[PDB]
Length: 146
Length: 146
Length: 146
Length: 146
Ligand SMILES: [Ca+2]
Ligand SMILES: [Ca+2]
Ligand SMILES: [Ca+2]
Ligand SMILES: [Ca+2]
Ligand SMILES: [Ca+2]
Ligand SMILES: [Ca+2]
Ligand SMILES: [Ca+2]
Ligand SMILES: [Ca+2]
Ligand SMILES: [Ca+2]
Ligand SMILES: [Ca+2]
Image 1: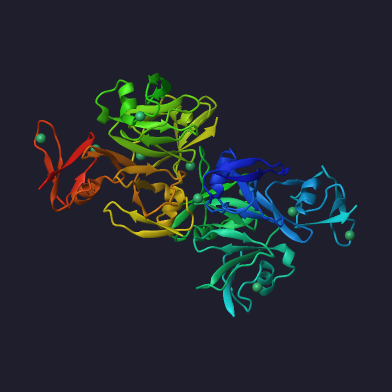
Image 2: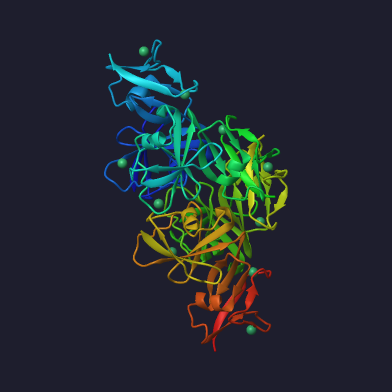
């Protein structure tokens, strides 16, 4: 019985055990106890903090060392954004600054995340400020040392 | 010099040659001659007609048999939808019915694509009708024989 | 003496006690007091509302926590159908809408079950309407919120 | 890469290789190259010649010794019948006598399969005679030595 960490839009971990060593996205969503399956987007959180979308029939090999990270969220569209030069797709419409800094792999307290707008003033997203990713265009976030 | 087929939101193929046998998404976007790189979403079109998103640093192994299929489109968000039970993410806001039926792997003329609304009348998308995927909720498309 | 809930085509529970902790389908049919054994189909009703057929020699482990659910019905053929994307086999030829919504795990009053016909009008099955599953093809039922 | 034998209503084997050690019925149907998934019934052919239905989300552990046997057939209903006292469900409406004797585990040439009708004359099914299982009632087949 392998184990994984199912997250949410707030990056709250939730250990879930699966008998299948190599389950599909549908199996992971079933294990998360979220229904219907078609309404939820699942992304594999790679060790380098990269969110790669996983499809309902795409298998994720859990038969490795360590507990894998999976982010399952109720979503109908994935919004693209850049955090510290890393491309990501967030399933949900709004993202908190603490989540952005966690994705950047930096200390939430020691760093401040800024939406970088070249030529204009950058917008500082607070730790618990739900910045809306629905804004037109790809969002470039950078974590400046506080 | 490997070769790939770069598509668009209209699924118009465009053969592009790359020296790198295993290039990244950034290299593919550069080869497509589309700038800036950050504004374009690239999806690998798998042989089973599955669009899997590819990231700017994720490598795509082109050193295989046959010409691989890549879809590069100017996009800031990926809209999720189901076509014949297959999960897909479309980079662009609008999709034509001919593209939907091509993704379904069926003859565009012999089939008609319907947005299935359980309990209500299904919406028939015409061959050159640009259905908007921005509609709230995941879209379920099914290709009924004409 | 373990206990189980023997159901019927109307999903009417009936507590039955068995001395054998791990009885076979034949033993369960005998405990249900239904003769001859060969004319009755038995399905284990899994906790996730999945009906999995059980054979006369296949053992069902009752030595677990909670009372298990068994559906025993006079049947010569199992008709396949999809309810909310879940595959099921109904032993009897006709199924009531209340049974469909119970299988879907939703409130019978708050939801309405529809036979989904892509491209055509969906057929609303009433709560006590005995829809015939003998219709050619696999039936796709979806419970829309009322 | 594990391997399985995908059969059909004529019990024609077809070796198929799967990367997933423990795939679901949906994965097996995908590997068989049969679409749509919802129209096909899959049954695990147990070593004792027992056909046990497998569901689209039910996992089949292939990580064992020997090549497992899977029967995938286009089916909307499973017809129940007894062959040599063994309960079976045939996905397709018609079954050939050679298939019946193969299920009985006996030599097709050395044995003759009879539909046993108590009190009346038993009906001998020929080797390549497509007996219809749609006949009302459970069919009891017995293989008498020729
Ligand atoms: Ca698996
Ligand atoms: Ca600035
Ligand atoms: Ca955005
Ligand atoms: Ca390279
Ligand atoms: Ca949508
Ligand atoms: Ca026992
Ligand atoms: Ca409809
Ligand atoms: Ca039917
Ligand atoms: Ca006789
Ligand atoms: Ca029959």
